[PDB]
Amino acid sequence: SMRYLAHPDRYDRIAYRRVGRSGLVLPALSLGLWHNFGDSTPIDTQRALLRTAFDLGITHFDLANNYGPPYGSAEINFGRLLREDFKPYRDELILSTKAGWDMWPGPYGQGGSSRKYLLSSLDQSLQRLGVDYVDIFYSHRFDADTPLEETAGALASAVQQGKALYVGISSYSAARTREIAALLRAWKVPLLIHQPAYNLFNRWAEHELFDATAELGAGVIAFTPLAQGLLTRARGLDAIARGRGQSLAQLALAWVLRDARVSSALLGASRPEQLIENVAALQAPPFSAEELAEIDRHAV
Amino acid sequence: GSMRYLAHPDRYDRIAYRRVGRSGLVLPALSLGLWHNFGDSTPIDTQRALLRTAFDLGITHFDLANNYGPPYGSAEINFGRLLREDFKPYRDELILSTKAGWDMWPGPYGQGGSSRKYLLSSLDQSLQRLGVDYVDIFYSHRFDADTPLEETAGALASAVQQGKALYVGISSYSAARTREIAALLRAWKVPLLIHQPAYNLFNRWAEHELFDATAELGAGVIAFTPLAQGLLQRARGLDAIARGRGQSLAQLALAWVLRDARVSSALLGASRPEQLIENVAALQAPPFSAEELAEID
Amino acid sequence: GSMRYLAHPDRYDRIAYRRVGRSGLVLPALSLGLWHNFGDSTPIDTQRALLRTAFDLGITHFDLANNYGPPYGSAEINFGRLLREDFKPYRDELILSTKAGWDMWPGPYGQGGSSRKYLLSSLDQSLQRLGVDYVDIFYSHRFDADTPLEETAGALASAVQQGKALYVGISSYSAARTREIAALLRAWKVPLLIHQPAYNLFNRWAEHELFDATAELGAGVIAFTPLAQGLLTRARGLDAIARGRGQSLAQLALAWVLRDARVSSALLGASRPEQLIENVAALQAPPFSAEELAEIDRHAV
Amino acid sequence: GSMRYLAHPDRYDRIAYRRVGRSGLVLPALSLGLWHNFGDSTPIDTQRALLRTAFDLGITHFDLANNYGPPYGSAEINFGRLLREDFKPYRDELILSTKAGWDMWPGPYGQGGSSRKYLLSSLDQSLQRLGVDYVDIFYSHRFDADTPLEETAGALASAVQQGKALYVGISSYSAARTREIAALLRAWKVPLLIHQPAYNLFNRWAEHELFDATAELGAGVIAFTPLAQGLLTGRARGLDAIARGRGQSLAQLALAWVLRDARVSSALLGASRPEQLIENVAALQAPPFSAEELAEID
Amino acid sequence: GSMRYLAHPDRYDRIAYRRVGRSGLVLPALSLGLWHNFGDSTPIDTQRALLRTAFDLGITHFDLANNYGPPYGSAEINFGRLLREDFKPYRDELILSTKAGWDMWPGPYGQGGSSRKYLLSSLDQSLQRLGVDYVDIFYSHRFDADTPLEETAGALASAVQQGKALYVGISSYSAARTREIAALLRAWKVPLLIHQPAYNLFNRWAEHELFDATAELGAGVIAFTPLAQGLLTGKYLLSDDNLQRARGLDAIARGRGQSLAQLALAWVLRDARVSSALLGASRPEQLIENVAALQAPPFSAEELAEIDR
Amino acid sequence: SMRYLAHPDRYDRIAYRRVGRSGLVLPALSLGLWHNFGDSTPIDTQRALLRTAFDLGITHFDLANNYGPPYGSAEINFGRLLREDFKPYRDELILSTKAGWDMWPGPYGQGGSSRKYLLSSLDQSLQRLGVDYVDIFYSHRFDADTPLEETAGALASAVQQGKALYVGISSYSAARTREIAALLRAWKVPLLIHQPAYNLFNRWAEHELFDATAELGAGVIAFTPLAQGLLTGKYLLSDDNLQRARGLDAIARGRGQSLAQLALAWVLRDARVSSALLGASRPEQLIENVAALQAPPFSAEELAEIDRHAVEG
């Protein structure tokens, strides 16, 4: 009876930004399957949100091995919706998975980033998603115990085995990013993208990190650009948002995307109607340096 | 079965074969390019007769692409069927090629580009539509200005290491960029086989610096649209030299684009089998002299 | 009635885990080896009960080999049957390792050796018998002076590149040759993870110069036969220190092997399910400080 | 089911095995080659009786090629059937090898050469006709003077990386040509294993500088046609006289004269009679030679 | 080294083969039932030796069941491994059988019965454990009084039509229940091949009605436990009067030049209406002795009345 | 390249006779792989003989599980030659396999007609041939120790499983042929064809068998029609048989035929017989026998002279 029909004007709604120096381009706003994508959410509300995201031009869906709840269920539910709805659009989509946090019991499945854990969890995500390969394979966290040469060798073996087109890191130190990226250069596989928690209440990336991502040629995607729903000090920024044609959440998305060194911001919305309003916030005129000074004072 | 394709017993004695630069691969002096008359618009009757006539003449190289049709990708689906039903015991004697660069499927990952994602995904689609394990030459159809050649070199190299292609080439690349991507492919220990520019009597653009680049790198050259998309004003004088030599202007241009060992082949479009056997007789001509070459310009 | 395998819920709160060299892998302080009492001469009842008890105590590493029997190769098809019936969901939680270097099948390409032909054929034999896509560690087993270490390192590198193995190991290798084969593997950008020497109270040859090599290269050590093949279960002066500190001679020898971070595991080959439980209780014993350690040196070397 | 191939239990106590170059492989002193009498023109029962005898005598190395027949490629089909019916549980005890470079299928891509196109497409044919996941030694049957050796070395290197061949060898190559292709193979970290030249008593060109080349490169040597294509079976009368003075035959003398040096690891005998292979194994048991016979052979 | 196993060349010149009733299938004079000492409690090398020894003796039929262990079904898993390693090139000359009637897995559909759900599901799992595409005979291990014999007959007939069994049979069935299920199998055009009762010197219930039913039907009979579970083997020199009757039967066996086990097996096979006799798992030299039970001369009328004490 | 192209006139050469009252039409002569197709004969002579056949119109090929030597090696060789040359022409051929005599050691392979031996030997022959179904599945001999209800039930299962399009029998007595046919009709799988040994010196099928095959509508295919020699002009056993063959050959040259052509035309003299297994021979000897029907039919005088040198029946 019912079948998914991708909107014909889906590629005339959002702007696609280059991921640093690499040829891959990501939509200005991506969708992160963090919230409301496990078994806790009905499937009809999951596919309705994913269809709305694709009709607006969002082609990147960021997943992880521990996304749920329970852990690993978001990849199963997205693997079904890719089998039933997004199958003729796979070559138009950009899927990514991570491995670093806690997944299954044991010292090999909780708090690790070794070659044993990375490759076993990548094969675990490929069988849950039902895809031949992932486009980006992050390292979900920095494991100070595991040497970064072993982690770089695991990400390199994943790209050589045709299971990952690119690789990246998530919430890594600014100096450790330079280390692992040069270790990937030894394997002749470039680093694609770095995922730091970038928003108005966390300046983690603005210090000593963007200088490293630009020289390496890697892009940046902002995890939780709305401070985990906090931007939905904040009461003062809402008055600045009312000075223009945007809301508090729309102003935060435009401020994270205010510069080209940021490729996208993982939205991770819940309802579809709020997704249509979060998307298409770039047509607002850029900050006049006047508004930038006001923002920097109200929020770090 | 009734009326199954049987290739000619002496099909390898009616056409010349030229080395592709400094490699071990040869190509027929005239190749067949399925740019037109091989989509779903053209009946299978003429497609089967044209591929059989080309293989009986000695043409073993069939040039395909992701956007060849129409519609896009249709020429690979039709050649994939013609390969399964006729050219199946002759697969190891053919030379198949496939490119990826122009607009293919909607989206920034399909409508143009030469990124790693688009190159390998379009190659997987081509291996699906052709029905082969690997292609013989995987081209980069266009030069991507907003994409590092180090990424494209890593994509073409991965296509060779994964067994999905024997050799790799580039199409419509500048003279300086051909040297750059060749030195990058040489970092992956995979040589750049062939280059496909638009060599033409009404163009002659690659002679400036591209021929000097491919000759020193060991990369062969194959001429694209050698008959000027139907042309071959100025064509009236060139037609006079052809009739005063025993050719039909089309045969003169084909013998001219292969007058030097730099060019290895040319991609004939063609529509009828009778004009294809006519063009093969272009190598049945005396070599060019100093007087005829001066009158060409 | 259905059997299944209800693994112990707090099985990871029982045994301690030690890091192997400067690598991301960790291993149980006590590893279970299928050297003996896992061939076809031992019933399936004993094999299944011992593997369930060892896993319920936190032992995840199960070290095997190609010639472990008797007969030769029976220990791998017995452990493979045990994997399909019990440890099928717990695959990613386990650490399986196989070796290839001793007498297997007749012929110069069989029997002893570590050539590229013998290593890849014996690895495909083990992967077919075990029923796993890959092994976590793959050792070279004994060293062969006739085969160049460039070909052995090339086969070990081709084993991890083909997805058949994740880590590379060696066993009973000379101290200098361990440095040589490690540098050749580092040329392939493939690290050496673990060396498995025979380390116990009566054979302390590894402390001479082998431990100084594994620590420098960043590779751990698994002590094969830490009880002198059953001789620690004159050593009666050691049996006096067994009554002291509240333990036994076997529990004293294990804790003595697990001194510093160089030793990552002690490959034990117990059989009785109850002695396996009492041997894991040898970790919480207090260290040897200085004087208690200087008493073991009387009846050592 | 009526009767299957039961290998001789004393097969590995018959022939002594020699090491090939500075590698881990150890080839037998004598190796049966399928150059002739293994096509469709030879009955199958004589092939099965000959291969059962070779393996019973301790021979573990079987040499094949893409063009062995007649017709071309039929020897790999006949050996493939005999493998799946008899030698299937003995697969890991054998050393199979195939060649590619002379004349196979019609066309410039098949009638010869050593291009990457022809080397991989002919190896795919050999792996499907033999019925094995890999050959043990993949050869380049002849040096291609018109194809750069950087491409042939790349094809031989990918043959090992794809798991199609454990080792790479060359055959009918020159002296400096072997050195320049082995130096290029050492860049891919796939060392050249063995060279297969024509080395017998009537053709001693390999002793010039090919023997010194393979000794320094670490590669072994296997002799092709040690009886000069059957001319030394039984001019040759002077060699037959020295053979009788030593207690052997002309075939056994020319066989032991090939295996006299350590840098000649094996010889490819292509006999047809099963009673003949048993009388060539009795050529290495004889005592070694000395001065008054080596200087008298010449 | 090399553990390849080839059967004895004279294995088919050892014992005789009796025809199953009036069909075409023959069975060895003594079969090998894997009831005891073939589960996970017994080492696999011991079972491997006993199977290789039995086949070299000519024993071609191997009687299995879904509950043979312990634990349940472990005998089918061990025989499946011994088949894929040793008995693979001898499959087309082996006769294999499996059953489904007693408690196997938890549940009302697993606590035994003759239902179509339990029969076809237990046969599918018994085919996976054995590693074979089909079994030669598929028994109905017990008679379920709560399930009609029309559903059980259609279940066995479905097993033959689906290529999972060549012949079918019934075990431990009544004499009237044998005539009933056989008459219903004639409707499916798949006749009842063989019946497996318990028949020995002490358990002679089948003589009254059963042997007459299988004769007029055309089926065969295979004798289960013809040694009364070690009571007719001299291992016990389970009541005192049972031990005294055994010593009396042994004295009549030593006058014939046999042992007590050889006497009981030859007594079971005294009439051609009986086709085989299941030999349990034992030591190899004990199987060699009991297999040579038909080599004795046939019983006389005075000897048969002498043992009918 | 070095492949096989069937002759275009192959279906305009030999005639085709209807198999009793069915829809199957076999060639007037067939090719049985009884001998000279095992591992003792080179595959090239087998290939050239199977290519000479079929080019002459020989579409039917008669095999058996024990055809060799060794036993079964003929089905393996014909399986390879079919996979290499005859794969596109598979639906234009009629392949048959049998099972009834000694095959593998044991009481279940040494002869018999039981359901176990028939289905096992059919699955063996299907794996060696490389085809998923044979066109005809014969019962090679009559088993007196096995009921015909079980043998007919095994043949009926072979058709319903998709492993055989039709079934037949060989060396069956006339009364036993009629009994197994009435049993097969209960399975709605009619008996297609019967294969008896029928030639000039062995005419037992004329007594009662040919009437049974005609009433049932089953065809007949003649096995050993040239009497394993003594009818091919090569021996020109026993001396009385040499005089009978010399007298028959004289009648053959009177009508322009050879001794082999005369015997093959005599077996095919009416519609009851449908074909005759020629067997392996040299290429020119196959072509000469194929055109045996190209001759005037037998008259009353010629048939009478032939009976003076043959047996009654």
Image (tube, coloured by chain):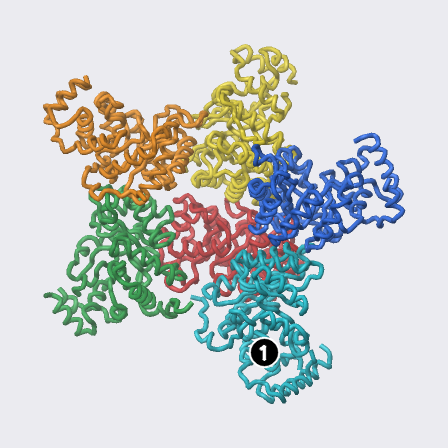
Chain colours: A orange, B green, C yellow, D red, E blue, F cyan
Label 1 Cα neighbours within 10 Å, binned few <14 / some 14-19 / many ≥20 = many
Q: Is residue A38 above or below residue F268?
A: above
> Where residue C283 appears, x then y in whole percent?
53, 17
Q: Is residue A152 above or below residue B30?
A: above
Could you say which is closer to the camera, residue E281 or residue B85?
Answer: E281
Looking at the image, residue B274 sits to the left or right of residue E111; the answer is: left
> Where residue B101 appears, x then y in whole percent?
24, 49
**Tag 1: residue type?**
Leu
Q: In which quadrant of the rendered view does residue D289 lie? A: bottom right
> Where residue E284 appears, x then y in whole percent?
74, 40
Residue named by callout 1: F268
Looking at the image, residue D121 sits to the left or right of residue A58; the answer is: right
Could you say which is closer to the camera, residue F19 or residue B201?
Answer: F19
Q: Residue at x 51, y 63 (%)?
A: F82
Subunit ID for the residue under disc 1: F
**Observer able to see residue D235:** no
Could you say which is closer to the camera, residue E15 or residue A207?
Answer: E15
**Which quadrant holds the N terminus of chain B?**
bottom left
> Where residue A125 appears, x then y in whole percent?
38, 35
**Observer able to see residue A109:** yes
Looking at the image, residue F60 sits to the left or right of residue C216; the answer is: right
Q: Residue at x 35, y 59 (%)?
A: B81
Q: Is residue E287 above or below residue B248?
A: above
Q: How many marks?
A: 1
Check disc 1 and report its element: helix, strand or loop.
Answer: loop
**Which quadrant holds the C terminus of chain B?**
bottom left
Could you say which is closer to the camera, residue D17 or residue D86?
Answer: D86
